[PDB]
Image: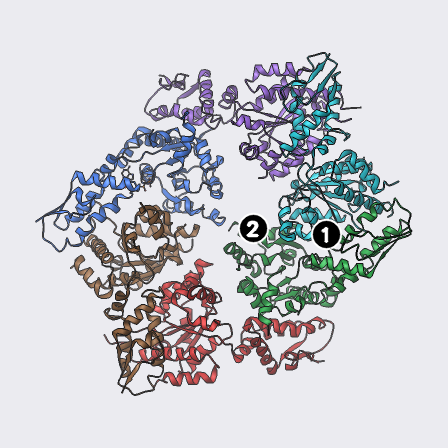
Chain colours: A purple, B cyan, C green, D blue, E brown, F red
Amino acid sequence: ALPTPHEIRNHLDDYVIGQEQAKKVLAVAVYNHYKRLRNGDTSVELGKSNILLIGPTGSGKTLLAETLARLLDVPFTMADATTLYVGEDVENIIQKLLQKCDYDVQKAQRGIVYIDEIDKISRKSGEGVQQALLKLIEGTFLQVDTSKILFICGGAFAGLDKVISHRVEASEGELLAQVEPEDLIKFGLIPEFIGRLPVVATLNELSEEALIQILKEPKNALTKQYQALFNLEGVDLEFRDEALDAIAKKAMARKTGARGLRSIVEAALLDTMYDLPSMEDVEKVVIDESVIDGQSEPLLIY
Amino acid sequence: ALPTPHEIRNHLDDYVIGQEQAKKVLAVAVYNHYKRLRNGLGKSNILLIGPTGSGKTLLAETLARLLDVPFTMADATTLTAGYVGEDVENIIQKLLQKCDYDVQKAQRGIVYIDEIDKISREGVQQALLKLIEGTLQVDTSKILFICGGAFAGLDKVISHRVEEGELLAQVEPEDLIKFGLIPEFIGRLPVVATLNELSEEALIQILKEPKNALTKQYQALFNLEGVDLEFRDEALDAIAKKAMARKTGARGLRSIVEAALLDTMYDLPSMEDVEKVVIDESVIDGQSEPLLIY
Amino acid sequence: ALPTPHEIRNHLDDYVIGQEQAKKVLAVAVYNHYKRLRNGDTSVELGKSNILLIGPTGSGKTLLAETLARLLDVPFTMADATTLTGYVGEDVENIIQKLLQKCDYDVQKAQRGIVYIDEIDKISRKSRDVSGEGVQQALLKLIEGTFLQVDTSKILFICGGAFAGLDKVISHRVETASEGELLAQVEPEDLIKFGLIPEFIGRLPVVATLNELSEEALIQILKEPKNALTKQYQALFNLEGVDLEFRDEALDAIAKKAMARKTGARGLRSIVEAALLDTMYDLPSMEDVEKVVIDESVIDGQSEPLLIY
Amino acid sequence: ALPTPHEIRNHLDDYVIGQEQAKKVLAVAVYNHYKRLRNGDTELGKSNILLIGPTGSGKTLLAETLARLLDVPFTMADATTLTAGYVGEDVENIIQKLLQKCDYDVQKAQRGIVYIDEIDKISREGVQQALLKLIEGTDTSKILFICGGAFAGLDKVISHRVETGSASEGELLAQVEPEDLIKFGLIPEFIGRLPVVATLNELSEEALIQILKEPKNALTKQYQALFNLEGVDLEFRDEALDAIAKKAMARKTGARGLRSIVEAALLDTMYDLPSMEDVEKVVIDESVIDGQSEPLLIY
Amino acid sequence: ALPTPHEIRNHLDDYVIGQEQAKKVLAVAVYNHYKRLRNGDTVELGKSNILLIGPTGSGKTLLAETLARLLDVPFTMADATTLGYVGEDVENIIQKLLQKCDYDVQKAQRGIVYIDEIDKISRKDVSGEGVQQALLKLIEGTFLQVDTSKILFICGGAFAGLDKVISHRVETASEGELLAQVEPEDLIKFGLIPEFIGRLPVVATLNELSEEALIQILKEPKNALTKQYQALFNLEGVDLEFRDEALDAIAKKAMARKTGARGLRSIVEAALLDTMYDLPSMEDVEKVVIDESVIDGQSEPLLIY
Amino acid sequence: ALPTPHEIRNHLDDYVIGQEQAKKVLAVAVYNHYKRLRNGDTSNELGKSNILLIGPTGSGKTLLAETLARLLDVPFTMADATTLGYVGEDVENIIQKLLQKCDYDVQKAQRGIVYIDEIDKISRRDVSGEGVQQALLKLIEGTFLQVDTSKILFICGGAFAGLDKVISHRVEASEGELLAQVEPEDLIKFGLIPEFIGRLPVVATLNELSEEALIQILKEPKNALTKQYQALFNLEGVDLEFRDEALDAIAKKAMARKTGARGLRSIVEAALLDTMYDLPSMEDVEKVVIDESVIDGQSEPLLIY
Ligand SMILES: Nc1ncnc2c1ncn2[C@@H]1O[C@H](COP(=O)(O)OP(=O)(O)O)[C@@H](O)[C@H]1O
C-alpha cells in the first residue's frame, strides 16, 4: 500500500522541521513516482517525476532523502557529484544500490538515489558527468534498468540566488521560489539534464538536527578534530548533546550555515586551549552554558 | 508511401503553432532526405535557430513520429574532450537501443543535437563532424542530423552586416562563421530553419494537441486516481500568458502546471470525488482552489 | 618512397578545385620539408620551409592542410590562433599533446606531423595588442623547436588566415588589378605593416596565395563535375518524372550570389536549396513535364520556376 | 620541550605591544601546530593562520618573532608578486628559499614558517588555487602558513551583515566570519585552509608612542645614539613623541611611517650638526607638528 | 677624516646644479652611512639607504657617481630592468664592485651601488617584484665572502605615475611641491612592496631643470660639454668659443624637446658636426659659435684666421 | 698620420654608395676616436665617441664597419647580439677573437674596432636579452687577456623596425627624414636602457640599400640563400649554379621593390619554383641560373645532362 502524500508529508514532520513547502513537493513527487512504478507506466506517457533539491548546506537535503526511503522501506544510496573512467564509476552507484538491496532486481528498481553537490559540476570534465549521470536517469552485468529508480539531486547553488534576481527584477526563500529551468541553464546546468528533473523543491530554513550531525557524524567533524587535539594533550574532550544543539542554534541565528560552525567552536575552546598546556587535569567537559551564555568556563575534571 | 511536404507540414500544424516558414523548410528538407534514401545527392542536414522554448526540440521529435522513425537527442555541451570522441558514438547506441538494434532502421533515424551554439569557439565541431559525413557498423551517412540552438549573439553579427524574425531570415553561412562555427561544419548543414518567439495560441496548442501534451499527462495521472481532470480553455490561455511574461517559452510550461496542481495532487488520494475542474482563477490568481465535483 | 611534387599536386586536384599555383607551392614546400627529414638534414644549412596560407574565408585553406596530411599518412592537428590570445604559453604545448594523441604517442611519427594554425591574421597587433603579439612569439618558440620530450623543429607548420587589410597595404606599395594579382605581389614587409612581427614572418619562408574564385570558375563547378549540384537536382527531379533545366542566366546568377557572400563554392549548395525549396515542396503534388529555373528565380527570388505541363 | 601558549604569548609581549587577543590566538595556533608535528599527528586540524590588520599594525613583526621564539626557519613572500601560469613554478620558489635559510635540511624545513603578505590583494583568483596546493602539501603539509593582509573593504562587508535594523573597527573585525571573506573575494576552498583567524587593532597613539621609546631598537634610541657619537645629547620631549604618533595615524602608515617622520624632522639638524660645537639638541613638539621652529640648541 | 655634510654638499655644487634640497639630503645620508661604518655600528643604527626620484636627465646618476669620487670609494651601477637565474646575476653587481676595488673586501664594503630604473620593476609583475625581494636580500646584507650590509645602496627612478598617486592623496602646485609630499604609502600603491621601501628610509627628490639651470650645466661643471669640445678643438690648434646667446639657445632647444640635460649632447654634436668634419682640412685661429648656428642651424660657425 | 675626416669619407665613397650624411658622421666619430688615443686622452675629459648605426637590412651597416677598419689598417671583428649568465663569459669571447686577428698584440688590439649587429633585437626573453645590454655595457666602459676595452671603438648596428613609429608619435615626411629626428629618448621607449644609450653618443642613420651589400648577403653568409638552394638541389643529384649576372639581377629586383633583404627569398623562390617542381621528374647533371631567368623571368634555367 502506497502512502498518500498527506501521510508522507506527515511522517516527514517527525524527522525534519520546517520546509513545509519542500516536503509538500517531495510528498507528491514521490507518491506519483511509485504510483507510476506499481503501474508499469502505461499499457500513453507519464512524468518521470525526478527531483532537484536546492537548499543551503545543512538545511536537511540529505536528511529528507534518507527519510523518504525509510518511510517506504526502499533501498537508499548516496553519491557525491564531486567524486564523479568515471563513466564506469557512475554505474557503481547501482551495484551499491543492489548491495543494500540484497541484489534483488525488482526492489532495486524501486530504490532511491541521492546525488549531492550537483551545483559543483556546473560548467561555468565535470560537465561530462552531467551526461554520464544523465544516462542513468533515462535508463539503459546488473541487467537492472535505471529508469524505475527515483533520482534526487541536491545542491546549495550559491550563485543561483543571483541569477534569479537579475531576471525577476525579498529574501532568498522568496527568490528561490521564482526559480526557473532557464535560471539553472545560466548557472551551468545543461538543458537536456534539467529537463530530466521536473520537480523542484527549495529549502529556505536550516535544520538544527542537520547541523548537529555535521558536528558529530562526519569522519572529519569539528568535535572529532578538537577531541583529537585535546587528545594529544592527554585531556579527553567531551561535547554534551545540549552543547552541540546550542552550537547549531548560534549558527542559524547568524545565517552563517555550516560554514559558521567552526568560528563558534573556536571561540568556545580558545580560552581552554590557551591555558591547557599549563595544567594537569584528566578531561574537559563542554556544556551548553559554555556555548550560549559563554559566561561559564568548560568543566574540568582533575 | 512517403508523405509529401504538404502532408508533413500539415501534421506539424497539429503539434506546433506558428513557425510556418520553419516548418515549410523542415518539410522539404525531411522529404528530400528520405526521398534520397529510398532510391539509393545532398546530405540535406538541418540547422535550427530559435529562442529557448520556441519549439526546436518539439519539431524534431514530431518529424520522427510522423515518419515512424527512431529518434534520439543529445546535448552538444556534453561533448565539449578527447574521450568524448568515443562518447560521440554513444548517440548511436542509444539510437539503436530505441531501434531494436536494426541497422537499416537505425540509418533512417533522426538525431537532434541541442546547444550547437554553445560549442562555438572547436574539437567537437570536427569530431561530431565525422558523423555528419558518415563513417555497430551503422553508417551515419544515412541518418538525418538536426542541430538546434538559440544563438544569442547571432542576432548582432547579422545586423552588423545587413546594415528579430526579419534579421534571422537574412542569416548567412558567413554569419555563423564569425559566430564561432567552423566552415567545414556549416557546409554540412545546408538547410537552416529559423523559429520566431512563440505566441499564446502557440503555447495553448502545445498544452493540448501533442500526443504527450502536459494536460494529457496530468489527465492520465489523475485518471489513475479515479478522478477526471478537466482543463478549461480560459485556464490554458491563462497558462500561456504566465509563460510569456516569464520569457521561459515552452520550457516554462511544466513549472507552471505543477505549481497549479500541486495542492490538488497532495490531498487528492485523501478524498473520494468524481472530477476536478481547473479554471483560470486557479492559474492566474492562484488564489481559488480547483473546482471539486463529488 | 616520397611522392614527387607532381604527384602531390595531382592528388590535391582530387580534393580541391582551382588554386593551381597555391597547390604548386604547397607541393614543393611539403616535398622539401620531408625530403629534409628523411635525409636527417645535413651531417650545412637547410630552410625551415614553414608555410603561410593567405586566402578568403572558405577558399579551402583548411581543406588543403588536411589533405596534405592524408596524402602522406601523417598525423594532423588544427588550432585557432584566436583561442591563444601567460597561461596560454602552457596551452601552446597543448597543440603538441593533441598531435601525439592522433599519433598514438609515437615520438618519431609525431615529429613528422603537420600543424595548422587558423586565423593568424587575427593576432596581428596593429592600428588586445600586447596579448595578441605575445602569442606570435609564444608560438614562435615552437617553429624553432625545443613531458613529451618531442621537438617541434621537425613538424611542419602551416599558418592560415584571410588577411582582410592585406589587400590594401600591398596596393599602397605596388602602386605606380584584381585581388589575385595583388596577393601575388605579397611581400614579407607587407605582412610587417599588417601587424606580424619580423621574427615571426622570417619563420614562414613559404607564402601561398589563394585567389578568390571567379564567376566562370563557380559556374563550371555547378555543371562540369560528375557530382555537380545541377546534376544532383536533375537526378532528384528525374525520379519525380520531372526534367529540371538550369538556364545559363541562372547558373551565373548563383555564382554572383556566392561571391557577394564570400562563401566561395561551399556556399553554392545553400543557395540552390533555397531556390528549389518551394518547388520540391509542392512537386509531388503535381503532374507536369519539366520545371525551368530562370535567373529571376535565383537573384530576385520573387518569381517561381517555370512549370511546363 | 615545546613552549606553552602562556610562554609564547609572554615572549611576544617583548617584541610587540598590544594585540593581546591576536597574540593569544597565535600562541594557541602555533603551539597546536608543533604539538601536532612532534607527535606525528595521529584527524587533526591543519591550524593555519590568517592575519587581518591595518598596515603597520605588526602583522609581519609577529610572524618573524614566532619563528625566532622557536628557532625555526622563517621566510616571507608577497602575494601581489604571484598574480600567471609560470608563477606556478614560482610558488615553489618560496620553498627553496625556506631551505636556503634552513641549510637545506628537509626535516627542519618542514618545521618552518611561511608568511604571505597582502593576501587581500589577490582577491578577485588563479593564485588562490595555486597557493592552495601548498597548504595541503605535495612536503608542504608540515610547514605553518600565515597569511597577512589589511583587507580594507572587509570592514564594510561585516557591517552589512552584523547590522541590526537601522562600534569601532576592533569590534567589527571580531565578528569576522568565513562567509565575509567569501564576499570579499577569497574562494571557499582557500579560506577553509585557514581555520585560525586573528584580528589586529590599529595601534593607538599610546601604542605608537611606546614603539618610539620602549623597544631596545626604538627610533629615539637610534638617533640618540647617532647624535651621541657627535658629542651631542638628543632629548625627545614627551610632547614631541605624541606629536609624531598623531602624524603617523593621520597618514594611516601605522608604525611603518614613523621613521619617515623622524628623519624629516631631524634632517636639517643632522646636516649642519657636524659644523657646530654645542652640548645638546632638544626636540619639542613645535619641531614636528608645525615643522616651522628649529630644535632647541644648547651649547 | 670624514667630510662634514657641509663639505659634501659644497663639492656637489661643483658637479651638479640646483637640487639643493636633494643634495642636502644625500649629504646627510652619506655622512651618516660612513659615520656608522667607521665607528662599527655600536644598540641599533639606521641603514640610511637612499631612494632617488627625479625626471630622466635630472642628474640622478651623476649625483651617485660624484658621491663616490668625493669619498674615493668604489662605485658601480646596475639597471633594475636586467634583474631565478638573475638571482645569481644580482651577486654580479658585487663582483663588479670588487673589480673596480681591486678585490679588497674592506674597501668593497665601503662601496656605493646605484640601481637605475627601480620604478620599472614595480608590480602595478611576477618576475618584476621578484627583484624587489631578491635585491632586497642585498640591502639587508649577506665567492667574495663580502657582506653587503656595509655598502650603501642608492636606487634611482623617474616614477612617472608617482606624481599622480600623491595628488590623489594630498588633495583637499608644481611637481617639485608634490614630490616633496611623497610618502612610503605612495610608493606602495605605485608598485613597490612594503618590505622593500622600509629598506630605503632616505628619499631624495629632484626637480626639473630650467633654462638658467641648463646653461650652467653647459659651462660650470668641470666636465661640461663646452669644456669638452673646447678641448677637442684645442688639440686642433683652434680655440672654440661659445657665445652666451648660443648657450641659452641650446637650453631652449633642450626644453622644447623635454629631453632635459640628457639631450644637451645630441644638440651640441649636430651643431659642431659640419665644423669637426672639415676642421682638420683648414688653418684657422678660432671658431666662434653664435646663436644663429644653434637655433636656426642655418648659418655656419664664425671662422677667424 | 691619421686620414682627415675628409679623406676618411672620401675612401668610403669607393666602397659604399650614398649615405653621405652617415659617412660624414662616421668619419668624424672615427677620427675623434683615434685622435683621442694617439694623444693618450688627457695627461694626469673626452667623449667615448662610440657609434650606433640605424638602417634597414642590407643598407650597408656591416660594410661600413669593415671598411673603416681596412682604411685604418686596424683589427676588426664582428658579433651578433642575438647569439649573445654563461654568455657573460661569451661576451669576452669577442675580445679573444679581436686578438686572434691582431696576432695577440695588446696595443694594436686596443686600437681595434668591434661591430655588434642586431642590437635592436635585445631591446626588452626580456630579462635575458636586456641583460646582454649591461653585460655588453661592461666592455664599452672598460675593465687572461689583460687588455682594456675602453680604447677599442664600438659600433652597434640594427634595423630598428618600430623606431620609425615611436619617433613619429613624438615629433608630431619620409622615413629618412624621421630617423634624422631620432633622439636618445626614442631609443629608450624602444627598449634600450638609459645607461646603455649614454654610451653611444654618436648615432648614424642609413636609408638606402646597396646592390653590392645585398649581393654579398646572397653568397657570403653561411646561411645564404644560394647556399641553401645549392644544398636542396644537391640532395637531388643536381648542382645549382648562380651566375654573377643573376645574383646582381636579384639585388636589383629587391631594391626596386624596397623590400630590402627580406624580399630576397621571395624573389629566388619564384625563379626556382618551376624548376623545383619538375626537377624530381628528370635526370640531369646541373641547372644554371642566368640573368635572363631572374629579370625577364622569361627564359628557363639552363639544364645540363
Ligand atoms: N606592535 C609593535 N611593536 C613594536 N614595533 C612594531 C609593532 N608593529 C610594527 N612595528 C614596527 O613597524 C615596522 C613595520 O611593521 P610591519 O611588520 O610592516 O607591520 P604590518 O605587518 O602591519 O605591515 C617594524 O619594523 C616594527 O619595528
**Horizontal and vertical percent for residue F20?**
44, 80
For image coordinates 39% across by 58% down, the residue present is E81
Looking at the image, residue B49 sits to the left or right of residue D148; the answer is right
Looking at the image, residue D45 sits to the left or right of residue B110; the answer is left
Identify the residue position indicated by label 1 in the image: B187
Q: Taking B121 as reference, is E74 above or below it? A: below
* Nearer the camera: disc 1 or disc 2: 1
Q: Quadrant of ligand 1?
A: top left
Q: Nearer the viewer, residue D262 or C147?
A: D262
Identify the residue position indicated by label 2 in the image: C91
Extreme-front residue of the structure: C303
Q: Taking C193 as reference, is A214 above or below it? A: above
How dense is the environment of label 2, judged by Cα within 10 Å: few (below 14), some, or many (20 and up)? some
Which of the chains bears the disc numbered 1?
B
Marker disc for residue D198: none
Q: Quadrant of the N terminus of chain C?
A: bottom right
For image coordinates 29% across by 84% down, the residue present is E303
Q: Nearer the viewer, residue E212 or D15?
A: E212
